[PDB]
Image (cartoon, helix red, strand yellow):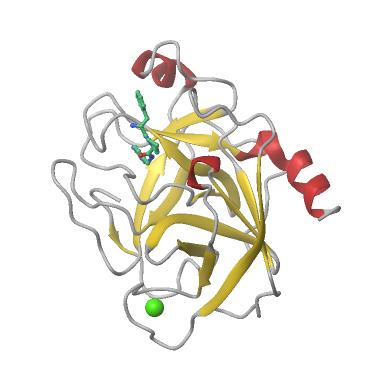
Length: 223
Ligand SMILES: Nc1ccc(CNC(=O)[C@@H]2CCCN2C(=O)[C@H](N)Cc2ccccc2)cn1
Ligand SMILES: [Ca+2]
């Protein structure tokens, strides 16, 4: 997260860190057994880390649970990043508490102009590299479809939306991949892609979760 703020420990209790020997992506806990992340975060050997603030120190509220199965969306296209969504099943159910909590799925899509919360442990620099240990947060509005398509001609599908600031300075970044965009108490986006971070006229692009609720519900009903 570039240009954001320190969230405060466990104040984003649905935020998870995906670990394969190191943090490599975020995700969102949607019930005690399932995490939503980005398809581009797929790899084998994932451990889901819940209850995290400082990802380099065991502070006492963590739950570390290995994934039993990952399911990349059947239509994910890694060339266009269309359908950039993946479900991860936990080997055992998380213990839900005030610091480890699920985020509701949307029933309707969010509106342009709505302010959302984006969070993660990704790079905090727009030029260069600095990775934080504690969870960072950003308030960012959903941008109009027109401005999103103008920023990325030929590349925005109906399964994507832009959020952030066309003037730059504030954005998600590498390492935030797969993490949540929460608007009005619902998981409306997944950190997906962009062009650099916090650059002028290149806002973050996010998977439009409301288009995937039927697939999520069906998949968790049979796995
Ligand atoms: N504002 C941001 C930007 C990035 C991220 C994290 N996500 C990534 O870094 C993903 C993972 C795979 C590569 N990637 C990218 O985004 C490529 N730049 C896409 C691209 C490729 C080619 C042309 C234009 C664009 C979050 N917030
Ligand atoms: Ca920790």
